[PDB]
Structure formats: structure tokens, C-alpha cells
Amino acid sequence: ETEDSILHQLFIVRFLGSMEVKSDDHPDVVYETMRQILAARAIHNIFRMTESHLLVTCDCLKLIDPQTQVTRLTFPLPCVVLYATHQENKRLFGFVLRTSSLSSVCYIFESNNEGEKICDSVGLAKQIALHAE
Amino acid sequence: DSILHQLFIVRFLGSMEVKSDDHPDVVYETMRQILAARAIHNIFRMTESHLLVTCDCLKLIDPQTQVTRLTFPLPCVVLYATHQENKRLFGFVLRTSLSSVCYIFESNNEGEKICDSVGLAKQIALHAELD
Image (cartoon, rainbow over all chains, first blue to last red; front, side, top):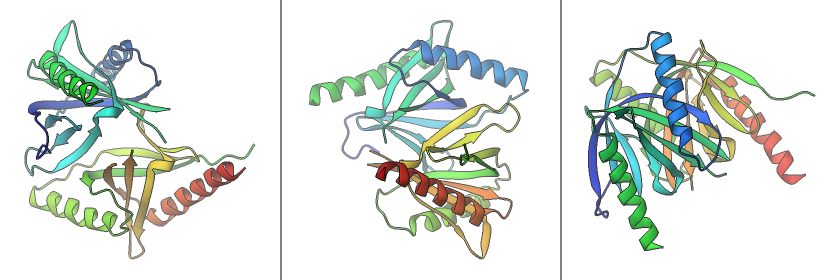
């Protein structure tokens, strides 16, 4: 977690869905995924949301099960290449995870109106890493 | 041309961050802990997907819409296993560079067929690397 990380910011999120995406450095990719995921959920009658905790640290983003406090998923910060909220709905937050063996997945979440706050927290973690450089 | 493109029905049971190491027991220890947690917390739900095995990657695909939900580069899949006496479980570790996550699935008694497929995928990929 953040034994050794100044940053340790926890957010309540609800996972909406993910898609494979093109590996580019364009933030419009997040918006397009949000559009596709939100449409697909509505059209296929997907209303179920499960609450997770999103942890932002200096080294990674983690998704934690609030029942068990078990880390279900971890995303190393260098691989989180794009992150954004939606100008027309700041409840939304998405990011792109780029893997190197080239392969990218965009992950979309809803929050309790914390899209901008999450983005600032990830942005701060990215800034620390650029300074450490 | 003949290409590896093998689909399997799988139901996702859970995943957890694990320590990065070649320790092959990691998948089985993860299986135990995920199964125990599901029992403790009275979890019934397990989302169905299609697992696609190719020489380049594993993908999880929405069975109804054919959308690729997740993709796992084959070189990052550093451990994978089923149980011979319980081929209704399949799991693997995805290692990104080191951070590792173990993913656990239920299969329709096809755990050995999945493992054989992923092994063939890895052989095809090794052939291209050596060429």
C-alpha cells in the first residue's frame, strides 16, 4: 500500500467496465470509452454496481474490496498513461493502463462526484514521479 | 493459414495482488484464499466471459456483445495452472514490469484443456522469437 509512500488517498468508486483500446497518448480515448461503456450498460440493462476503494499511492493505483480489505487489482503508476474525468459528468473517472511485453485497456468508474479530485491525486502522484526522475 | 484462436467459457471468481516471484504454488494459494473469501461473504455471483487464447495474448470477451473487456499479453502470463483432480478451476499470474496479479476462474471442467491451449500459444510465440 503506502508503508513507504507520502500519498495514500482512498476514494469510493464503482467499476462500470473496461475495454481494450488503441495504444496512443490521446486523452480523447478515455472519453470515447466512457461513451461506449455507458451506452452498452444502458442498452444491455446493466444496472449493478459494486463499490470498491481506489487507492492512489506514489507507486500505483490499487483497487481494494471494502469487505475484506484485500487488494484485488494493482496498476503500476508508470503504466497509467492517461486519466480523466468527463466535463459533462464529474462523477466519472477513467484511466488507460498500457502494458509493455503495445497493449492498452481503459477502465471506467463512477464516484461520489470525485472525478476531478481523483484526477488531481493521480496527477500529483505522476508529478512526484517526474521529480524523482 | 492455420492460427491458434481457441475460445473457452469461464466464470470469473476473483483476483488478488500477489508477490512477484516464479513460485508456482502462488496460483493454488490464491485459489484457496479467493474460494474461502467467497464462502465467508456468501458470494454467489461469478461473471461469465469468453476466454480467447492466441499466440499473442489472452483476452476476456463479453459473450453477448463480443466486446474485449480485458487483454493479457502472453509474455506477461508467467504462471498458469489448473488442478488435475479439480479441472473446474483455472488461474494465472499476470506480471507487469514488478507488479503481479493472480486471476482465478471457474471452467466447465476444461481447466486442463485451457492449460494445454495456453502452452501451445507459448510454443507458437517462442517459435516466432527464435525465428
